[PDB]
Length: 210
Length: 211
Ligand SMILES: C[C@H]1O[C@H](O[C@H]2[C@H](O)[C@@H](CO)O[C@H](O)[C@H]2O[C@H]2O[C@H](CO)[C@H](O)[C@H](O)[C@H]2O)[C@H](O)C[C@H]1O
Image (cartoon, rainbow over all chains, first blue to last red; front, side, top):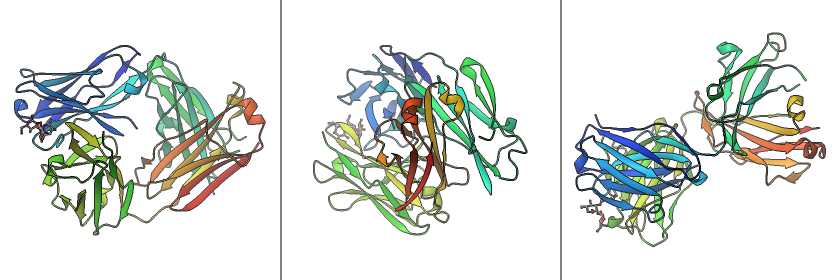
């Protein structure tokens, strides 16, 4: 049916430039506008291209930054972003538009991160307190995303909360918690397992009373 | 320029009718502004709803309708379902730019309200050993998904040094979020009492510890 397929995750340095792609399927490309949308934790319109006659509209704010193109042959629209800064880190969407609208069907979004940080392993710390008890693990200072966290090698699935990463001093920090019966710990061990594939890190942290 | 304004959060019950509005700083919204409405669900899942002021996009349920109600564009959901709990953004075509509203968080009460479980954890000794101190406040199981987090160090409000994640949806459809206070072990040792204060639906939950 209609599908707008986007390219994947991009990692880039300051000053550099990147090209993102968006392929149309289930409709005639040349009769619709392909728009591009920036999401940074608010939404902003970048601009739009009409592939049948290659007309474009830009947001004035993005005129110096973006270049939109389309190939009616490979049914792909493209966006070039140049002179990257950290302010360009955001998720970007391409959307299908027509008369009076910009986006009935949306792509899934391609994530862009602009950073000069290098690949760093996480430092993992146990979070002990000292009816039910809540234990946690802090995954601090890693780059890039993602880390995965299991508890007791996946055995402890129930009551587990892994939080979204926040950026602190250009590296990520994440935490995960598990709540277990208070009669169960310290008696039955609780270990968090953190893997960070980019730095091929695999670390286990037993939670011990304080 | 033009600023587009929307309610920031609305709450309704399943079966009820709710209306979301979209106003512009350049005066009345008209037809030539082609008001668009779209929906954001958990995990960057966007769905176009309304195009050109009132056209339903393909496969949008008929309970969603768009209209002008006076000087404003509005989205009316007649008979709201639990799956309509989402962020709704309007946009207007103005001076050859699509300009976005801030988005409205709509809660459609699919289950009873739930107060947050707040846990505050001290820095681990292993971290202190690196000359750093991070306090972690985890906030889970609250519904509606709207929370304000404040940090207090010896009663003084903390204005720098903390990070809070945007509320995230749990698998049981309640919400969770975490907040961090990072200090150097020297600032950590200069104060006795630390508090994580979470306000949900007018009520505050406070968790405190002492060094
Ligand atoms: C990108 C842009 O696409 C749509 O507007 C276009 C119209 O559909 C076509 C034909 O009707 O003409 C123009 O290329 C676009 O018109 C928009 O811009 C004109 C410029 O004179 C006017 O402002 C029109 O009101 C406006 O529709 C879509 O409707 C809006 C936008 O996403």
